[PDB]
Length: 56
Length: 224
Image (cartoon, rainbow over all chains, first blue to last red; front, side, top):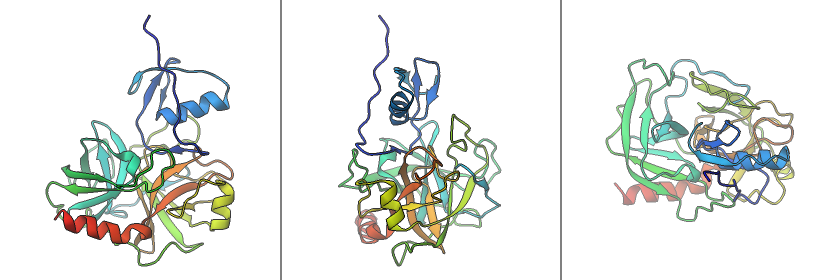
């Protein structure tokens, strides 16, 4: 089809880089970077995908 | 910056932004031709903007200067963020005035409890997305290494420290990486990472510039 890439994390730690490098979620929400998105999917037990790079 | 305030005029003349068609990190002017930021801010092309306050409305003293050379620390670790530091050589020299000027490197490592001023155009909201027009400033003190490493067990290397408040509510946030942590006139820290922004028991962690003082001058000298 035309689907979204699963977000993933690299920082084997308790936190995320503080860059702004947004990505656009399949939920329609712009997340400031990919790391912050995988943390929300962990925290809120959701599974937002990456529709495309950049803002929504 | 969460829980900060609008920087007064010419309060942070060393503040710059790094740009790739949008504002994505901060940085600090440490030499007429050099800016220091975080290693995770690396991009293959970067435009540096100096002397801003309002990032959407030109006030007239802005300088737009593309990076000539972009040097990520040679031992940068993407997975742990150890050595999250970077040098940028401007392709022309900044004009020094009241709104654009350099900041000294630190003559001693951070001292627990010293008050620092942290600044940038990053997120002002702890939940969601609220990115400000006006340059943001936050006074926040250096936290003890007991407090810092208890806050982030096993993940704080000797090239890192914590600045802020353990009770949360005031922190740097996304878009602030690369920006300065300035204490008593010295660049002690670079905005690097944290667990979210302004959470209880999760203060910002910042790269300790003192540990790279020698590398910075040496690396600058070789490319001058």
